[PDB]
Structure formats: C-alpha cells, structure tokens
Image: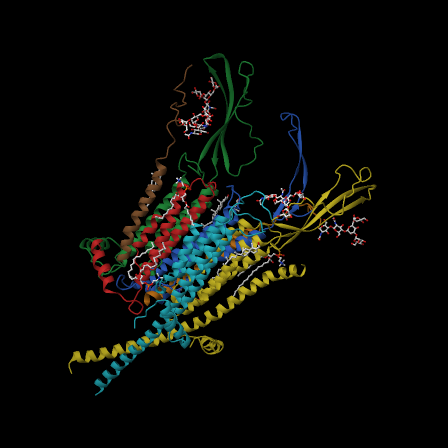
Chain colours: A yellow, B green, C blue, D red, E orange, F brown, G cyan
Amino acid sequence: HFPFDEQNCSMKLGTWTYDGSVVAINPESDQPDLSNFMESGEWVIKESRGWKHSVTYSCCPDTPYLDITYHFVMQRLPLYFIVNVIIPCLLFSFLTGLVFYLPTDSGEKMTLSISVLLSLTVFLLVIVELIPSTSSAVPLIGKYMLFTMVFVIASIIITVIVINTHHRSPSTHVMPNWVRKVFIDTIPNIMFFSTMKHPEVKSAIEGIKYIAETMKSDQESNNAAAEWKYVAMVMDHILLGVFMLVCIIGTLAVFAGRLIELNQQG
Amino acid sequence: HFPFDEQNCSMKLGTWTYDGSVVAINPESDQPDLSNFMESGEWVIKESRGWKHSVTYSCCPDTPYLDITYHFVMQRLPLYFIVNVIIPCLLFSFLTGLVFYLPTDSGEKMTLSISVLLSLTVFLLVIVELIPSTSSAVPLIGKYMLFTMVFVIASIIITVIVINTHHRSPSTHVMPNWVRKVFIDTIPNIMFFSTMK
Amino acid sequence: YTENGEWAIDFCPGVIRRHHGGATDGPGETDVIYSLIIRRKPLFYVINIIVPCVLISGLVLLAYFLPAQAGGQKCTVSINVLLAQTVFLFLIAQKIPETSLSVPLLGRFLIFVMVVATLIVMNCVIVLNVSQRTPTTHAMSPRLRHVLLELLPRLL
Amino acid sequence: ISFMVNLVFYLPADSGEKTSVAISVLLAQSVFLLLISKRLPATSMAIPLIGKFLLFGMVLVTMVVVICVIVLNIHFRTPSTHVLSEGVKKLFLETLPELLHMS
Amino acid sequence: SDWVRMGNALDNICFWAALVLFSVGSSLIFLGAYFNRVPDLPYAPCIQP
Amino acid sequence: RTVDRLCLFVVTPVMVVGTAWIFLQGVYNQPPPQPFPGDPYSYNVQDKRFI
Amino acid sequence: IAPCILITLLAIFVFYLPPDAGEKMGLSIFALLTLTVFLLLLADKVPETSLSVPIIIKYLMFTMVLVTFSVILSVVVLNLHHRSPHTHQMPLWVRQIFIHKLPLYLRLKRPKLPELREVVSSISYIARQLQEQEDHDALKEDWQFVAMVVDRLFLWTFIIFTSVGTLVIFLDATYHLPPPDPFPSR
Ligand SMILES: *[C@@H]1O[C@H](CO)[C@@H](O[C@@H]2O[C@H](CO)[C@@H](O[C@@H]3O[C@H](CO[C@H]4O[C@H](CO)[C@@H](O)[C@H](O)[C@@H]4O)[C@@H](O)[C@H](O[C@H]4O[C@H](CO)[C@@H](O)[C@H](O)[C@@H]4O)[C@@H]3O)[C@H](O)[C@H]2NC(C)=O)[C@H](O)[C@H]1NC(C)=O
Ligand SMILES: *[C@@H]1O[C@H](CO)[C@@H](O[C@@H]2O[C@H](CO)[C@@H](O[C@@H]3O[C@H](CO[C@H]4O[C@H](CO)[C@@H](O)[C@H](O)[C@@H]4O)[C@@H](O)[C@H](O[C@H]4O[C@H](CO)[C@@H](O)[C@H](O)[C@@H]4O)[C@@H]3O)[C@H](O)[C@H]2NC(C)=O)[C@H](O)[C@H]1NC(C)=O
Ligand SMILES: *[C@@H]1O[C@H](CO)[C@@H](O[C@@H]2O[C@H](CO)[C@@H](O[C@@H]3O[C@H](CO[C@H]4O[C@H](CO)[C@@H](O)[C@H](O)[C@@H]4O)[C@@H](O)[C@H](O[C@H]4O[C@H](CO)[C@@H](O)[C@H](O)[C@@H]4O)[C@@H]3O)[C@H](O)[C@H]2NC(C)=O)[C@H](O)[C@H]1NC(C)=O
Ligand SMILES: *[C@@H]1O[C@H](CO)[C@@H](O[C@@H]2O[C@H](CO)[C@@H](O[C@@H]3O[C@H](CO[C@H]4O[C@H](CO)[C@@H](O)[C@H](O)[C@@H]4O)[C@@H](O)[C@H](O[C@H]4O[C@H](CO)[C@@H](O)[C@H](O)[C@@H]4O)[C@@H]3O)[C@H](O)[C@H]2NC(C)=O)[C@H](O)[C@H]1NC(C)=O
Ligand SMILES: CCCCCCCC/C=C/CCCCCCCC(=O)O[C@@H](COC(=O)CCCCCCCCCCCCCCC)COP(=O)([O-])OCC[N+](C)(C)C
Ligand SMILES: CC(C)CCC[C@@H](C)[C@H]1CC[C@H]2[C@@H]3CC=C4C[C@@H](O)CC[C@]4(C)[C@H]3CC[C@]12C
Ligand SMILES: CC(C)CCC[C@@H](C)[C@H]1CC[C@H]2[C@@H]3CC=C4C[C@@H](O)CC[C@]4(C)[C@H]3CC[C@]12C
Ligand SMILES: CC(C)CCC[C@@H](C)[C@H]1CC[C@H]2[C@@H]3CC=C4C[C@@H](O)CC[C@]4(C)[C@H]3CC[C@]12C
Ligand SMILES: CC(C)CCC[C@@H](C)[C@H]1CC[C@H]2[C@@H]3CC=C4C[C@@H](O)CC[C@]4(C)[C@H]3CC[C@]12C
C-alpha cells in the first residue's frame, strides 16, 4: 500500500545467557514510554504495546526462556510521495490522451506522444531516486507508474494506427465495406460534434479537355482520401473519450481501494 | 590507456623508529605469497616482486635505513567499460553520419542530429560517473567521447549549411558560376552518376 | 525468520575441510565452510526496468508503419527511442555490478536493443531517401523497380 | 552546444526545425546544470564561473527561442491575417538587406 | 508515386526482418535466464516448507 | 529572413564576447606570488632566513 | 528559479507561434521535459518529510501545471486551425463570439458544334471547381481566424495567470523573514 502503508515493527528483548529460572524479566508498563518522543515528519505511531512471552521446551521443562517484545504500529505520512511522485504521473497520464484531439495534418502527433514518453522516462529516474527498491511486492506507486507507462505505449501504438489510416492512399488501398459501414454510417449516429481546323486548334481543344479531366480525377482522388481522413477522425474522437475514461478509472481503481479503507478505519 | 591501462602500485614497508643497525629486515621470499589470493573481477596481477632497499645518508653513515617494497603489476579487465561506455559511443558515432543520407525535404535532419547530440549529452552523465576525475592525462574513453561530441557538433553545423543551400531560390540568391562548375559539372563525373544532372 | 526482500535462501550445506596435513605442508589446517545458495527475486527489475525498456524498445517497430513523407515523423520515433534507451542506460548503470568477468543480462539486452534501434534508424533513413526521390534530381533506376514492385509480390 | 544555438538564425523558416533546435540546446544546458549541481557546495558567497556561463547561456538561448518564435510568426503572415505596410517593405526589403550585404 | 511504392515495399519487408531480429534476440537473451535455475543439489532445503 | 540576419549579427557577437569575458576571468586567475599579501617573504626552501 | 522563469516565458511565447509552423507541440513538450530534468535536480536537495510542502516544490508543480495547460490549449488551437471545412459546419454562436465580438476587444483587425460545346463544358467545369475551391478556402480562413483569436485569448490569459501566480509565490517567499526576537510571544 506504499505510500499509504501501515507497518507493524517489533523489538524482542531478553537475557541472552540467563533463563527465567535464574533471572526473571517483567515489563515496567503495558505500553512503551512515549512521553519524551520527538515528533516524526514521516510516520505516525497509531499503537504501541509491550508483551511478555515465556517459552519452555520438553528437553528443559524447568527452565523457561523469557522475552519482552515491544511492537509499534506506524502509519506513513504520504504527502511527500503524493506531491513529488503521483502528481507528475497524473499530469503525464492526462497529457497522454490529448494526442487523440491533435489533428494528423498538424504533423506533431508523434512529437507529442514520444515526448510525453521521454518525459515519463526521465521522471523514472526521479521515481527510482525517491521510492525504495524492493522485490517483496509491487508497491501502489509501482502499479500506478507501470499503468501510466502502458497507457503511454498504447497511446503511441494507436496513434500510429490512426496516422496510418489517415494517410491511406486511395490508389494502393481500397476501402473495405466494413470500415465504411462501421465508421461512416453507424458510429457518427452517436457523434454529437461538428463532424459531417488546323492541327494546333485541335491540340488546344484536347488540351482544355485534358485539363478538365485532370481536375476531375484529382477531385475524385481527393474525395477518396477525405473518406479515409474522416474515418481516422472518427477513431480519434472515440479514442480521446476512451483514453480520458481509462485514465480516470485507472487512477481510481489503483488508489481508491486503500483510500476508502483508510477513510473507513479513521 | 584507460580502460586498457596497466598499473604498477607498491607497498613500502619498514620499521618506523628503528634503523638498520638495530633491526634488520629481509624478505621471506622473492615474490609475495599469492597462494590464497581471491580472484578479482576487475584486475589481473601480471607480475609481483618484493625488493629490499638500503639508504645511507652522509650525516649518519653507520645507520642505514631499510625497507622492503612489494610491487604488483596489474592489468585492468576492460569488458565492463567496453560494453557500457565504448559501444554506445560507437553507435552514436555511426548515427552521426546517417543525417547526410536523409533528404532535406523530410524535415527530419535536425531532429536526427539534435537527438543524437541529446543522447550524447545524457550519456555524459554515465561517462563522468564512470571516468576517473583526474587531470594527469586525458583517458582514452575521454578522447573518444570528445571526438564523438565534436564531430556530431560539426555534423550539425554542416547540416544547417546544407539545408540553407537546399532551400535557396532565385527570389533570394543567384547561383555563382564557381558553385555550378564545382558541384554540378566536375564532381558528378567522378561519382556513381545515378542522379541525373 | 523473515526472508530478505530481494534474496531467498535455497540451500546452506556445511562442510569441515582438512588440508596441509602432508609432511612438506607441515602442521595440518582445518576450517568450516557454509555455502549459502541464495536466489534473487527479480520483481523490482521486472516491473521498474525490464518491462518499460522492452516496450520502449519495441516501439521502433512502429516506425515501419508511419508514412515516408515530411509529416510522418518516422525518424522522430526511432531516434527518440534511442534517446530513451540512453536514459535507461544511465538508470541501469546505478544498479549493475562493476566487474568484467562477464556481461550481465540486463546490459546485454540493453545493448542489443540499442543496436537494433540504430539499425532501424538507418533503415528508416534509407526508406525515406528512396521514397522522396523526384525526377528533378534522380533518374528512375529500373533494376530496383523490377526487384521491389514486380518481382517481390510474385515471389511473395 | 551553447554556441550551437546561433545556427538557428541561418536555418530557413520553411524547414520547420528552428525552435526544436533552440529548445533542445536549452535542454542540454539543463542537463549540464544537473551535472554541475552534484559537484559543488550550495554556498552563496559567489556564483561559480561555470555557473555564470550556464546562466548566461540559458538566458541567451531563451532569448533566441523568443526571437525564433517572432521570426516564424512574421514568416507565416498572409494577406488574409495581416497587412504588409509600405513602411515595413521599405525598411526590411531595401535598406536593411543592403546595409547587411545580403544577397 | 512509383518511388513511394518502392519505399513502401522496402518498409514492408524490413518490418518483418526487424520483427524477427528483435523477437529472436530478446527471446534468446531471456531464455538464457529461464534455464538458469538453482541446480538440483543433493541437500535438503535450508528452510523446511 | 532580414530579421533573422539582423538577429544573427546582433546575438552571436554578444554570446562570443560574454563567453570570452566570463572564461577570461578564470583563465588569468592565479594565486598571488607570495603566500601572505603584505609579506614579501616567499616561504621557500631557497630563501632561508638565517639567524 | 531562473531556469523555471525562462521556461515559463517560453511557455507563454508558444501562443505567439503560428499554427502553420508545426512547432507548438515540440516547444511546449520540451519545456515540460526540461522541467522534469529540474525535478530530477531537486530530488537530491529537498527534505523528505511530509508535514508540509516546500514552496520551491509548489513553484515547480505550478510551472509544470502551467506548461501542461499550455500543451493542452495548443492542442485546442491546432484542432481549431486544422479543422476540415467540409466535415465541420461552424456554429453561428462560434462565428458571433470569435469573429465579431472578441476580435475588437483583443485588438485583432481582420482585413476585409461538338467542339464549342465541349469547350464550354470544360471551361464551365473548371470555373465551377475553382469557385468551390474559393468557398472552401473562405471557410478554412474562417476556421483559421477563429483559431488565431482563441490563441491570442489564451496568450493573454496565460500572461495574467503566470503573473499572478508568480507574484503570489515570490512575495510569499520574499516576506518570510527570520524572527526579530528568539522567543516570540504566541
Ligand atoms: C504486531 O506484532 C506483534 C507481535 O510482534 C503483535 O503482538 C501481539 O499482540 C497480541 C494482542 O493483540 C498478543 O496476544 C496476547 O498475548 C497475551 C500474552 O500471551 C503470552 O503470555 C501467555 C501467558 O499465559 C501465554 O499463554 C502466551 O503463549 C504468550 O506467551 C495474552 O494474555 C493475551 O490473551 C488475550 O487474548 C486471548 C485471545 O487471543 C484471550 O483468550 C485472553 O483472555 C486475553 O484477552 C493475548 O493472547 C500477542 O502475544 C502479541 N505477540 C507478540 C509476539 O508480542 C501485535 O498485535 C501486532 N500488531 C498488529 C498486527 O496490529
Ligand atoms: C614498479 O615499480 C617498482 C618500484 O619502482 C619497480 O621495482 C624495481 O624493479 C627493479 C627490477 O626491474 C629493481 O631493480 C633491481 O634491484 C635489485 C636489488 O638488489 C639488491 O642488492 C643491491 C646490491 O647488490 C642493492 O643495491 C639493492 O638495493 C638490493 O638490496 C638488483 O639486484 C637488480 O639487478 C638487476 O639490474 C642490474 C643492473 O642495474 C644487473 O646487473 C643485475 O644482473 C640485475 O639484472 C635490479 O637493479 C628495483 O630495485 C625495484 N625498485 C623498487 C623500489 O622495488 C618495478 O619493477 C615496477 N614494475 C614494473 C614497471 O614492471
Ligand atoms: C591564506 O589564509 C591565511 C589565513 O588562514 C592568510 O593569512 C592571513 O594573512 C593576512 C595578511 O597577510 C594576515 O593579516 C595580517 O595580520 C598582521 C598581524 O595581526 C596580528 O597582530 C596584531 C598586532 O600586531 C593584532 O592586532 C591582530 O589582531 C593580529 O593578532 C597585521 O599586522 C596585518 O596588517 C595588515 O593589514 C592591515 C589592515 O588592512 C594594514 O593596516 C596593515 O598595514 C597590513 O597591511 C594583517 O592584518 C592574517 O593574520 C593571516 N592569517 C593567519 C596568519 O592566520 C593568507 O594571507 C592567505 N593566503 C592567500 C594567498 O590568500
Ligand atoms: C525556538 O525553539 C524554542 C524551543 O522550542 C522556542 O522556545 C520556546 O518559546 C516559547 C515562546 O517564547 C516559550 O513559551 C513561553 O514560556 C514561558 C515560560 O514558561 C516556563 O515557565 C513557566 C512558569 O513561569 C512554566 O509553567 C512553563 O512550563 C515553562 O517552564 C511562558 O511564560 C509563556 O507563556 C506566556 O506566553 C504565552 C504565549 O503568548 C501565553 O499563552 C501565556 O499565557 C503566557 O502569557 C510561554 O509559554 C517556550 O517555553 C520556549 N521553549 C523553551 C525555552 O524550551 C523558541 O521560541 C523558538 N524560536 C523561534 C521559533 O523564534
Ligand atoms: C529579445 C526579445 C525581443 C526580441 C524582439 C525582436 C523583434 C524583431 C523585429 C520585428 C519587426 C517586425 C516588423 C513587422 C511588424 C511591424 C508592426 C508591429 O510591430 O506589429 C506586429 C508585431 O511585430 C513584432 O515583431 C512586434 C514586436 C515583437 C512582439 C512580441 C512581444 C514583444 C517582444 C518579445 C518579448 C520581450 C520580453 C521577453 C523576452 C526577453 C504585429 O503585432 P500583432 O501580432 O498584431 O500583435 C502583437 C501583440 N502581442 C505582442 C501582445 C502578442
Ligand atoms: C566547432 C567544431 C568543429 C568543434 C571544435 C572543437 C574544438 C574547439 C576543441 C576540440 C578539442 C579541444 C581541445 C582539447 C584540449 C585542450 C587542452 C587544454 O589546454 C584546453 C584547450 C584544448 C587545446 C582544447 C581547445 C578546444 C578544442 C580544440
Ligand atoms: C552488438 C550485438 C550483436 C550484441 C550485444 C550484446 C553484447 C554485449 C554481447 C554479445 C556477445 C557477448 C560475448 C559472448 C561471450 C563472451 C565470453 C565470456 O567468457 C565473457 C563474455 C563475452 C565476451 C560476451 C560479452 C557480451 C557480448 C559481447
Ligand atoms: C543478443 C543476440 C543478438 C546474440 C546472443 C548470442 C548468445 C549466444 C550469447 C549472448 C551472451 C552470451 C553469454 C555471455 C556470458 C557468458 C558467461 C561465460 O562464463 C560463459 C558464456 C556465456 C554464458 C555466454 C554464452 C553465449 C551468449 C548467451
Ligand atoms: C500550484 C498548483 C496549481 C499545483 C501544485 C499543488 C501544490 C502547491 C499543493 C498540492 C498539495 C498541497 C498541500 C496539501 C496540504 C498541506 C498541509 C497544510 O500545511 C496546508 C498546506 C499544504 C502543505 C498544501 C500546500 C500546497 C500543495 C503542496
């Protein structure tokens, strides 16, 4: 649950070379003395208590072995990690979805996406510098950071797909019927946006006719390309919505469980 | 010659307060005892030898000063620095020249060159944390990194000049005769000539 | 016993050794040697370094799908993946051991993906150079045209 | 690397890679500042010479980025968005080019 | 357009070449680790399960 | 283009002169000839001050 | 502090960069990357406690949020600029607010016989195509002017928001003087 983690840490004390039959130990009080305890800027001691334990073995039934274990329940103060780790990750995650609102014709989609990835990679140095590095379990910070990384990678891949769809040449590529039905016909129904008699004389005559046919063919080619551009624009809208939803719900699914648990337990 | 360097360090031993006329020292053996020497993951001991030395000063000719000096010739194992330092520098050096095969109309020449420069700048962190921070001489890795940095910088300068030349138009400039003769006439004759004049 | 956060103790045999008992050796010697066989739990390196590095290094394959035009940003993607790999090199330099008896797997993988990224950068540069040729500067080579456009689809 | 920022003035505005070069030089200077920050104490008696150069270079590179933004803004003007007065044409196409020995 | 088609064909074949290289090399590097388990020694575990 | 050329010829000399001044302050920085200002003695082995 | 100020100035100046240059995103996002480098710089210096946030950390996060908003609103401006005229119909309220009302307040002045039959057909077709091109260009110019007006509005808004936030933080830091008396009365 780091940095919202609670730690139970003990201190077992006993006479190393004397057993309970020659030296008996008893706690002075049921709790440790915290009267002169200096406040900690990183931890809060919720509970503290000292328990006496006696252990006897069948080999030595007349010599019990005594110890006093003091344990402290400590709760981490998470403000430092919230401010220095979580907020930049949230900003990068929010910026991840903005590429789907950035038009392909700007020529800056990969700039934005790859540079967000670069900023996250550079911030990974900060992540390693700040949080501890252990393999006992995946921390909550680690889960959120990995989620953000996968979010950025998926955004980059889907952005490349969208750009490729945008630049589909109408000559080499022909439109599948399923793409037309899904994206031009069905999906826009739920889209509430702004979307949708000398030889020389004869040569001159043929030249004007050829120019007219050239402009006509260019018009058809541009319309066919514009269909692909419209398709990519529909995918971009849906992906913007989906990625903004995934960002919010991923943040909630990561943190809200432990946050609600701590809220309910005071 | 770092990281392919060979180092000769010794250990000078002697009685601090006793001269040779009261306490005499002699080595047990010609060489240090290395029978129980644990393997080193960074150095190989090529040679080892212990030498006795006697120093007499004119002030006190009858009181020699003795010492036994054990020296060790050590060769660095360079695989770590080859893998971590030299190979990335070689990759950046190779990437430096690829900008000159990029078309100017791509609008990616500066992106490539500047990103290579930025990679080298980030790599300077690795090198300065790894390189010895001493001024006795330039380490060989330091020379190679300075080479790569200087020549990616030169590539950036020349790429800017090439882009400027590519974008020229009669509305801003006029082709001089010498440029035309040098670049359009003579050089293509001694080239592959696949590109038409 | 609380297991170490990174290391699991699998085996720990003990042996009593005796040596130097020969006449030339002189008085015999003995010792006790315990061999702690410990296994690393690699979860931290998997989550924090290896998986992000693998994904960022796989991104260069996407450069093959971008258009070979001014707005394609094919070289943008490849060289920035190389830059991110350099950042990961700085990250990994703080963790790996600093011996030279062998190359660690993490370093080997990082250098391999860096070499692959460099080759893909060269490949993208070549593809761009081929794609944006115009008749005002280049003459149409028919050998390459036949090899790529006519022979290849029929061979495929 | 700091002197490399001056090449942006010789880059044409149609290349579309000017502010990228300048801001990348700024990023490299920031990396060098990070490198130097680990090597000296944080005393206030004086600014180090290398620190003085780095601050001066960062300020100059920032000014160069601003200049590049302004130059691109001027370059991409058209009749439908701006009006080109005769005074600007006289100053910037006749007098300054011949003063500066431009082609 | 012929030049663009040639570039597209080169990019298509080179994608598969690069994918095979990346996959095979990464798989070999990590399979080196997958076969690096602790050897089956003739001793009991240090900690009883 | 004219604005760019003017900015080149205005900005590059400023950069060069500022860098040169900043680094020349350090290039010609040496400790004083004597260890103690105001004391002409060099505190060297050659210049022994015999009683 | 000084690099952060310079980065903030560049983030402001993004909004003066024309959309046609195709360079807004690079400048804004590399400013963000430089700020990330400076966050790495501060990680080795700042205290690790959680009772409060250092004011320099507050300034760094404020600058990061400013650059993030500059990125977001540059994306908005580019979306408006590159808007395809035939796929979008400009709403009338957009026309009113962003072409008639706001530009005055932002000081943006917008300036302003088979052969013969086949000849007639071809010429008429070419003229009709060019007229359609002119109409398309007019709608595109309307969208681009809306983008320019929105860009100027965001430029002024960023100047105001940067000035206010920077002044608040800097005055909070400046007027934190040590106590005149070692044992003040509370
Ligand atoms: C963090 O970790 C520490 C351990 O390091 C935990 O400490 C334990 O706390 C519990 C109480 O919550 C202790 O349990 C109590 O122990 C008392 C003493 O037991 C010793 O002495 C008796 C003598 O007869 C022996 O029989 C016994 O074996 C021990 O040697 C008991 O008297 C208590 O009894 C109470 O509870 C039982 C039911 O459990 C009732 O039947 C009784 O009537 C009575 O109400 C109790 O068992 C435990 O011993 C502590 N362990 C140690 C090692 O100190 C912390 O609780 C933990 N913190 C967390 C996770 O919040
Ligand atoms: C790393 O650095 C160390 C220290 O500088 C070097 O050690 C020196 O190694 C050389 C050998 O290459 C040593 O020189 C040898 O010294 C012997 C000393 O003999 C003793 O007896 C004489 C009186 O007879 C005394 O004066 C002396 O102090 C000793 O008590 C000599 O016997 C050797 O003789 C060899 O050279 C002479 C000619 O000079 C020949 O006539 C002989 O046949 C023979 O070949 C020799 O002079 C030197 O003393 C070492 N110095 C120290 C300080 O230990 C390492 O060599 C170096 N490692 C590298 C760079 O590889
Ligand atoms: C490296 O660092 C060391 C210190 O660690 C410097 O040494 C100091 O050098 C200065 C200048 O040489 C010394 O200051 C001088 O002290 C003299 C003696 O003062 C003592 O005696 C008088 C009574 O006779 C007492 O009142 C006084 O408190 C001291 O106990 C003075 O006579 C010198 O006077 C000079 O300065 C005054 C004021 O400007 C003038 O009016 C005089 O004419 C004259 O010029 C002077 O004040 C200082 O004591 C040294 N510190 C030590 C030895 O610890 C090195 O100079 C420095 N090296 C470099 C290269 O920077
Ligand atoms: C740096 O850190 C030190 C230590 O933390 C601070 O020192 C504390 O300063 C405060 C404020 O000056 C002190 O609090 C005051 O103590 C006075 C004396 O209290 C002692 O004596 C009385 C009996 O006469 C005992 O009952 C008491 O326990 C103490 O032994 C009180 O008289 C003061 O009360 C008056 O002022 C307060 C506030 O206005 C009113 O509410 C009261 O009604 C009354 O008028 C007051 O409590 C405190 O004792 C100091 N701690 C020490 C000395 O250890 C420094 O102030 C701090 N420096 C900074 C931040 O600048
Ligand atoms: C070193 C920094 C300064 C470099 C200056 C280089 C100049 C080179 C020479 C430029 C010659 C231009 C000739 C053609 C235009 C003539 C008419 C005219 O002036 O109006 C045009 C502006 O044209 C300008 O260039 C105005 C000056 C720059 C404005 C940017 C902000 C101030 C400078 C940067 C900040 C300095 C402090 C912070 C950084 C240190 C049209 O104006 P507008 O677009 O309709 O309205 C602008 C309104 N706005 C300003 C609110 C957006
Ligand atoms: C602009 C492009 C071509 C790069 C130019 C690099 C030049 C300026 C660099 C590269 C190597 C440098 C030299 C490397 C080492 C030394 C020795 C020492 O006494 C400092 C100066 C001196 C002599 C340097 C002077 C400047 C230098 C020659
Ligand atoms: C450049 C690409 C192809 C490979 C990238 C990985 C590099 C670092 C790998 C490939 C082959 C590897 C070598 C293969 C075998 C040996 C012998 C062994 O006794 C020591 C390590 C050493 C010398 C390896 C060092 C690391 C190495 C050089
Ligand atoms: C990465 C791709 C491209 C190339 C892979 C080549 C393979 C065969 C190389 C890469 C790394 C190499 C290993 C690196 C180091 C060692 C340790 C040494 O004591 C024995 C050989 C051994 C175990 C090598 C065996 C061969 C090896 C596995
Ligand atoms: C600048 C804005 C836009 C973005 C960054 C938000 C920063 C400044 C916020 C996030 C969390 C905040 C802290 C949350 C709680 C506390 C504890 C108490 O002592 C009040 C102030 C203090 C210490 C806040 C100071 C401001 C703070 C650090």
Q: Residue at x 47, y 52 (%)?
A: G170
Q: Residue at x 23, y 62 (%)?
A: D87
Q: Residue at x 45, y 56 (%)?
A: G32
Pick whichever, B94 or D68, lies toward us. Answer: D68
- In this image, A16 relative to B150: left or right? right
Question: Residue A86 at x, y = what percent?
Answer: 54, 57
Quadrant hosting ligand 9: bottom right
- Residue furthest toward the left? A198
Question: Residue G117 at x, y = what percent?
Answer: 23, 86
- Residue furthest toward the front? G185
Can residue B87 be spotted in the picture? no
Task: Give the quarter of the image for residue F21.
Answer: top left
Can residue A219 be spotted in the picture? yes
Task: Give the quarter of the image for residue C131.
Answer: bottom left
- In this image, A163 relative to G131: left or right? right
Pick whichever, C149 or C3, lies toward us. Answer: C3
- In this image, F40 relative to D97: left or right? right
Establish if A246 lies above or below B9. below
Pick whichever, G27 or A46, lies toward us. Answer: A46
- Residue furthest toward the bottom? G113
- In this image, B53 relative to A256: left or right? left
Question: Residue D96 at x, y = what percent?
Answer: 23, 56
- Residue furthest toward the top? B62
| Number of disc labels | 0
Question: Residue A127 at x, y = what percent?
Answer: 53, 52
